Image (tube, rainbow over all chains, first blue to last red; front, side, top):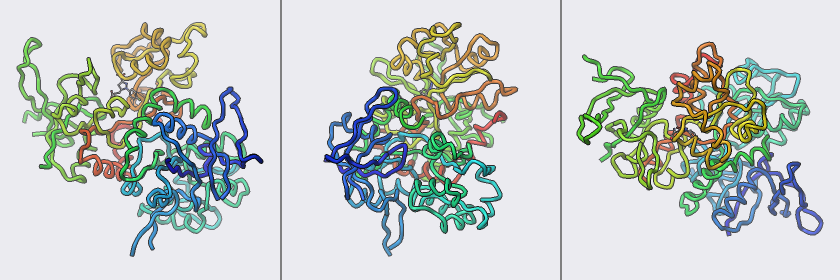
Length: 269
Length: 278
Ligand SMILES: N[C@H](Cc1cc(C(=O)O)nn1-c1ccc(F)cc1)C(=O)O
């Protein structure tokens, strides 16, 4: 029984409360497709999980013939390596390496730092980084003076302990930017996104697969339109790992037979 | 030891082939040999020396410096990227599966069939099945209704691809009637399809996304455009093919991921792939 870990990140993973009798509400899409829901335990109630990644997990489950239990990441983070001396990963990366999870099914960004300790599938989503703001405030992009040389007058940050945080730490050139960001980062994208609507946050550097969808739904928000950096999401497995080849082979098959497009049509478009 | 046989395949701007200086390989190029046939009635031939440059070649140079290896580059003589013919591979993939090359460097698309017989590195450029039109034509992507049921529109859209590749094979398995209708508009090659769009005989050309983005970016007057990258079908990428269980895959992956993370990848893409248009 595979222990799947994941994280609240719409439109890839929705997390909604359980009905009184321990079950999930049955729902169909507007195009008449059943919205598959799985029980996911998380911070420790059972809850209802569905979305882009859940559909993908179900296909991977049935294609490779395995059962699973899904739980939400304990600390709520994607995962960066931090010092203790010794080092340890937090977030979903920590739970995968520690055995709390056998496989990560989430919008987990593939990068060099994580790829040295875990195995990544071929990407199930091709993607990038962009900036989300409120309608009214307009920014050139990644090179607007309001972010290059920052200030307290214009605030901008990303999600704490995420791939974006890793991206802005490793670069000697983004030092001035990351200085402003580390004192303003958020524990989750939803909190940051909500902060932009509340005007307490002025810009949000985050995953375009999330930000653009958040703009197509919440019309009180828009993004830059640019993609200043491109990255992909992958399935995370331990270094062993008997599932690495077939999970990856199944991601490639799902792209080629239109499955990934139908997922994109259901959740991201 | 760590001296590697590497196969490649000409496809500008990813691999560009030049003759030798008359008069050693020149500047931006690396030596790449090509076994040239004497005629078509014999297997007899001669190793011709040539010079290879381009996007993927720069990748090869960066990998050689980082992963620390030496190599003999050569161009594939039989086939293109790789196609299983009667369960027998040819092209760049063939050189790997049958162990004449330890890795393949080029515009080699990662798919499921090839990943069964070879190992692929992480993708170093995004590609897929995309659509190119003239400015002013409104189409979503491959799965647009004006492509799946062309005769639902009057007049029907005129669109095709270059046959016998991964594009035609993908469309035939996924949309049988689309493939049936679009046979009539099969193009001889990429350049012929461009001219067909420019002169109005074609309404759309379905092909490799990375190739179409490069052509649309270089097009004179910028009249040809591709759909948004969000509507690319069967998204995937060009990757390095290695032998199954190759010991080089891990270090190639981390080096490739390093180039993406430290900007060395974006630099190569403006030195080779970015054009006048947008
Ligand atoms: N680099 C070629 C693939 C390329 C050749 C052609 C063609 O001749 O039809 N179309 N594609 C292509 C098809 C599907 C994708 F997702 C991306 C590219 C290769 O490696 O074979």
